[PDB]
Length: 9
Length: 9
Length: 228
Length: 228
Ligand SMILES: *Cc1ccc(S(=O)(=O)N2CCC(O)CC2)cc1
Ligand SMILES: *Cc1ccc(S(=O)(=O)N2CCC(O)CC2)cc1
Ligand SMILES: [Ca+2]
Ligand SMILES: [Ca+2]
Ligand SMILES: [Cl-]
Ligand SMILES: [Cl-]
Ligand SMILES: [Cl-]
Ligand SMILES: [Cl-]
Image (tube, rainbow over all chains, first blue to last red; front, side, top):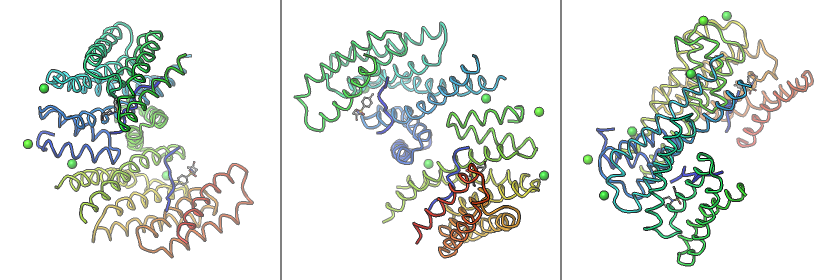
């Protein structure tokens, strides 16, 4: 299952 | 130009 | 970073992101938060991106080490090194939680800022829960749940169902239900309802907002495909 | 890492590589070197892999920052942050060079170990040269050249032309000639002669050695394709 990647502005 | 990647044992 | 100007810290955080120097990015953004002013939308995203990258690398390393350790359980070095990485991960989570507690959440009055920070609070308690055992696991799980629930309550009252932060909050809370709380049915129900209510609101959006919302909806659908 | 056993440091370096924790890997291998015993073939590779990954990330960040800085030259923050990354990169190179000088090279009597360490010495002086300016650039360039040349002289006397370390040394020295020393013709000649002499020796190799040698030969050919 994936959460928000959230690693790029 | 590439040198030896050298980043994996 | 007390001697550096706030604006210089923000500028350097943006440079560190371009250079893929996420530890530096996080340190610059911690310094910016500690100047004591509220953060703009863009600055909140820089803070979040920085720490998500730092803790994401730690979590991936912890999972590799925990897998090796479990296989060896089928000298002390694997456990010792997993413990070292785990302590560093917990320290980063504690640092982010401390920024949120001193004083980002209490100064956040608009729904957009308050939801964003409460979602972060849920996420960093969830990362603590991933490595916790036993009874401290219980209290950490409840802290994550409570943060996400407060964020959900505000988001449902104050934001449209397509708002990307509302969508990402629901996505991450659904992951919490599935992976942490042992509530796969709650995870599936939340993802389904979120997806459906967003779909019904897409007609209100511009082309650019539509792209933002549908990108996160696809993540909800990807989880539903895996879970059902 | 003075209180940790040598064998535990090596074991943890291998775990850190699997976890993609290259800074930890390098610290474990530095501790292992500082125990004062010579390194085995496998341990030399762990040391090299660790530092190549650390300095590789720094070099990539420095190039991003230097590009932004040059575009701005067509406040002080870009230069300050490039300088910060540059200083950290120079510190890592100095650390590796200091391990080689105290005392890995002087204790290396077999050709395989001595060539490996002198190739490392050339490489870390080359990384210093990439960020150096002016006259200190000259002396750093000469230190790289001298290390590579000594390694080449030993390798040509003591190793077959297909030996992977001899091949990688020649590849990296050719890159030095092309990118650092402003000697593209010397770079092309060295890569061509190295490739041709290796090709003529492939018939002597087992299937596994053939794969090892041909992989590096392909890198020489890839550079020749770009340079000619
Ligand atoms: C939790 C979360 C993080 C990031 C996003 S986003 O990538 O859609 N984006 C929303 C608009 C803002 O600029 C912040 C980043 C959604 C949810
Ligand atoms: C400089 C250099 C590094 C690595 C290699 S390698 O990947 O072919 N390999 C050679 C055999 C040893 O096990 C060391 C690693 C070649 C050159
Ligand atoms: Ca100021
Ligand atoms: Ca001992
Ligand atoms: Cl450890
Ligand atoms: Cl406020
Ligand atoms: Cl700086
Ligand atoms: Cl010796």
